[PDB]
Amino acid sequence: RRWCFRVCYRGFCYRKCR
Image 1: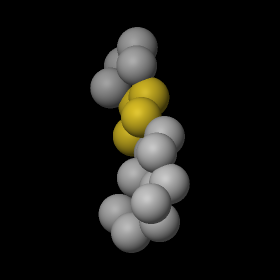
Image 2: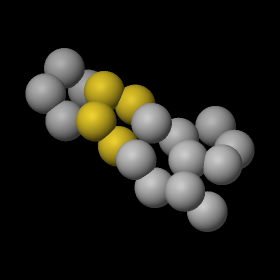
Image 3: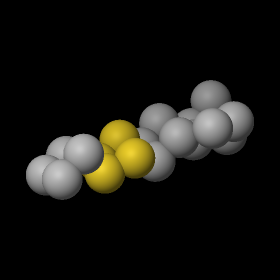
Image 4: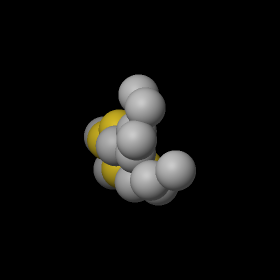
């Protein structure tokens, strides 16, 4: 949420700052 989301889906975690 805002500035990078970061979210682990029990195997894959997101990570994009923008």
